[PDB]
Image (cartoon, rainbow over all chains, first blue to last red; front, side):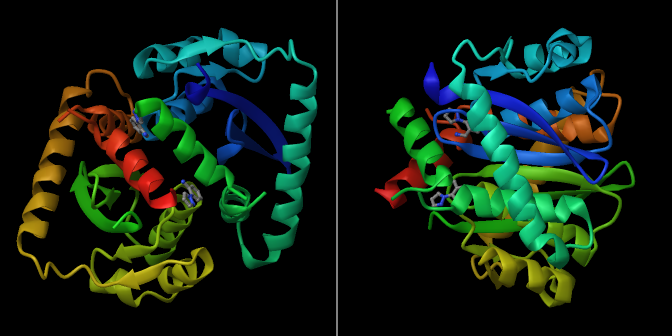
Length: 150
Length: 149
Ligand SMILES: NCc1ccccc1-n1cccn1
Ligand SMILES: NCc1ccccc1-n1cccn1
């Protein structure tokens, strides 16, 4: 069920890890910088995400988080069906790779306005979610979920 | 108005919980920080505005209203920074009640969370999903979609 499906994506920059959740139907994202991708960090990130949007399904980004006791506990807590993230559809991989490159591009564009990477990454989530493509991802996610409520 | 949010700062366990409340829906986002500083408040608003279409923020106190760093984040993110004076007195009573509701929920999830920050996000989840028959999560999405269309 499309309005509730999200994909986790973990990318690296400046020796740090950027954890992203993409709402697959809209391209809307939330993202955080963490020191490393552990079960505990992923779990807490999912808890935050599910408190903010109606997360029904998550495609986890790798098998360590799919396996992780802590990730499973957060998904049980927040009512999330944890799935694998295998691109049975191959164009999925490319879409995510392209967002990572686009996100890193926006990060380079603001990187000097931000003393800390975390700032630059939240600036990048803002520019990504507001970019008009004519609707933005922030507009599409709202539209998709509102249609689903009604 | 679909773009109006209120900042709210409450204390528990010697730590600070910063809350943004979407006024029309009651939907919230919240974070634990060591201390309410301009830099923390700025970063929190930047995150909030990248996630929801934040047009106006009622700041929670005059230090954040004044803060250069808060004004810079509001300029960067396109937010009109306002004072949070309850020109309607029922506004402050609504925030007090939510801080008490939030603290209650945090109490109820204390067996389950080792760190306060986990309990606070559990409390955000339960607050936003609570049916009152729509939830706050439902109302904000409905409000903002009506706005877009
Ligand atoms: N809808 C959530 C959202 C999130 C991020 C950025 C923008 C938005 N948006 C909605 C209407 C207009 N922008
Ligand atoms: N809409 C954002 C949201 C956030 C938190 C909890 C629930 C929701 N929601 C929307 C539709 C159904 N639940």
